[PDB]
Structures are given as C-alpha cells and as structure tokens.
Amino acid sequence: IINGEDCSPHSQPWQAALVMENELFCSGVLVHPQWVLSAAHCFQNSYTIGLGLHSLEADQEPGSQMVEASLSVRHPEYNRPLLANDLMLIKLDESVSESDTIRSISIASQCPTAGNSCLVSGWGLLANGRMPTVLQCVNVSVVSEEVCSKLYDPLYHPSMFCAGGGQDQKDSCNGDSGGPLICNGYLQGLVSFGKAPCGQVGVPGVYTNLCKFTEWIEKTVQA
Ligand SMILES: NC(=[NH2+])c1ccc(N)cc1
Ligand SMILES: [Cl-]
Ligand code: NA
Ligand code: NA
Ligand code: NI
Ligand code: NI
Image (cartoon, rainbow, N blue to C red; front, side, top):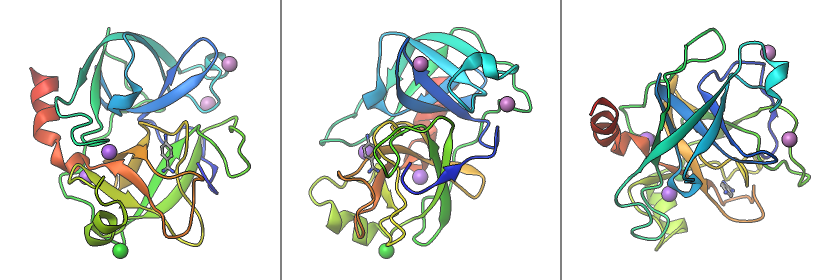
C-alpha cells in the first residue's frame, strides 16, 4: 500500500491473507462464511488462508483463524482479453466462525462512480519499497470509466475500474493483489494491477469490477 497508514487493528474484518510458509503472496476477501474471494492471478492448488490478522503472525491474534482450502473456482473468462475478469472464489474446507475480528462483507450492487472516496488495504509494498509489518489502509478515489478506458487502452475491459492516480500518490502495489477496495461499506473491487513504479500521478491502479459479477458469485457460492 503506497502512502497509507497502519489500519486500526481488526477494522477490516473481511481481510484474508493468502500465505505460504515464508511469504505472503496475495490477499483475499471473505464474502461468505465458507468462501474467500481473490484475484484469479493469485491461484494455487491449495491455500493456507489467514483471517483476523493484523500482523501476519497468527499467535499474536487470539481470534485469528488460519484455514485450509483446495477448491478454487476462477471466472471462466479470466485473462480474456489480457488481464480481464480477474476474480476467483476459494471454498474453504470448513466455514469460518464469524466474530468481532472476522466477518464477511457483501459485494457492491452499485457500480463504481467517479469521485467515490474508497478504501484499499493490504500487506503489500510500501512507498520505500519495503513490506509493512501490519495491515495498511489508504483512501483512493474512483476514476471515471471514460478516463480509465482511455488511459489503459487496449487493456481496459468492463470487468475493470480505476481508482487513485492523484498527486497524493496513494495506490496499492505488489503484494496487495486480491485485497479489498471498499466503497460505501461494500466490497467494490479487488486489487488487480497497475503500473510500476506504483503511485505515479495520473496513473491509477486497476481493480476487478465486482458489481459485474455478483450473479456469477451468487451462483458459484450457492450452488
Ligand atoms: N495498483 C498497483 N500499482 C498494483 C496492484 C497490484 C500489483 N500486483 C502491482 C501493482
Ligand atoms: Cl475521472
Ligand atoms: Na483486471
Ligand atoms: Na464494482
Ligand atoms: Ni514469516
Ligand atoms: Ni488483535
């Protein structure tokens, strides 16, 4: 997360860490007691998913739940065209027990409107190039589809939307993949991609446009 601040502990209860024995390669979002949503480029045959974390050390959180998962359902149009339809549903082995620090969030029905003040969180790269020790939070504003489409042409696809790109240089970055972008108390997008270096002025990050997939998500989860 570029130019953000430590989030208040457990203030983003839907945040999930997709981790390995040594690294953290992506985040995800709890959208149902038994399902975590993430970017399709974060795919793995199996996952160790960390919920209720602030620092990435599970023992530091009495309420943290590290859960296993091996079933992933990627959107069938992922990467067609290049980089589009960047989402995947990970079905946990067992439902998580929702608590004060762990909670699923609903997906936005309304599509992103330019100027909305939203929040993105993650454990990815900071402005100095180092990784944080705890979950980072930053506000970024949604950019119009007209600007997004022209800035990223021909990579822009309706399954994407742009946020950020201001002089404040706030942006998400490597390691924030699959993490949430929250607008109006709803999950509006997933950190998908952008340009390097992160946080260039006039270059907003790109996010998965979830308002375009609620039906597919509902169908996958429920069935
Ligand atoms: N928004 C970005 N600059 C970004 C997001 C994800 C990522 N893997 C790399 C860069
Ligand atoms: Cl705009
Ligand atoms: Na995308
Ligand atoms: Na959306
Ligand atoms: Ni470690
Ligand atoms: Ni805590």
